[PDB]
Image (cartoon, rainbow, N blue to C red; front, side, top):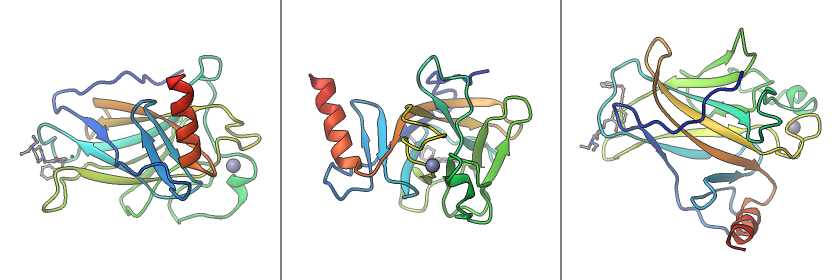
Length: 196
Ligand SMILES: CCN(CC)C1CCN(Cc2cc(C#CCOc3ccccc3)cc(I)c2O)CC1
Ligand SMILES: [Zn+2]
């Protein structure tokens, strides 16, 4: 089955936010609002903001999952390729098969769904650091979009869900991802293709 990707702010007014990192050739992570698409280098830090209008209950969690964007591929589980799943770049918590990791959160949990076989990573939803207006999660993507035997050039979406302590839906947002060598150039290219 295919998880829903419908944007849903829910009772707490949940939505994501992204930094404005620009498109210099050296940039390692950059988000395009026009494309709703994050471009990032392999295994590099991707800051994703969580914004709410009101405080969700203690025990609320935030889950990330990848799916293929194209209709003809949506039913296939997104996983790391046969090379990367074996490169022993473990952080001690993430299964080596999982495309999406949360970086630097000891409370991260990784799920292999018993029915759909899909992978996800979930962390507690926490209030912002003192002085801040939103909470930031740092994600890593552990294969290139081009990895043979993995994503194999097929575009993916990351779905972020706000969940209660039982796993029930409280909110949902999503964005496309391209993991590539030169996120700055690729964002510029794709934005120009869109303008054309
Ligand atoms: C005054 C401005 N107004 C927005 C208009 C508020 C700003 C303050 N924020 C608080 C806030 C809580 C949370 C959370 C949580 C669950 O854990 C809890 C742990 C302990 C206690 C409660 C919850 C996540 C986020 I992201 C977040 O912004 C809520 C919105
Ligand atoms: Zn790979």
